[PDB]
Image (cartoon, rainbow, N blue to C red; front, side, top):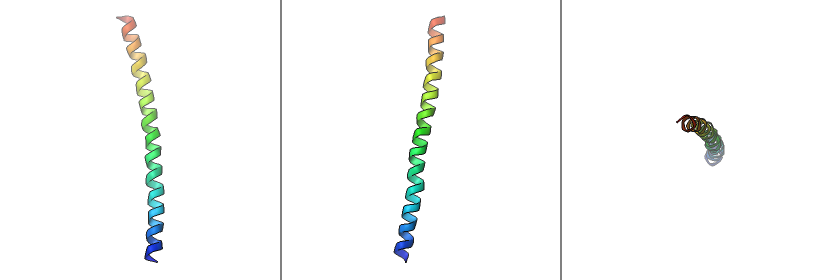
Length: 50
């Protein structure tokens, strides 16, 4: 019973923690994309003005 309680704990925490890992991985990806595109358009405007 302790083994199955542990295994339930392992599958539950593994599921929520790994899904948090990929979810914040894509969150990091879209934050990088919006920051990169903002810096790209700003640097392009800066260089075209200079």
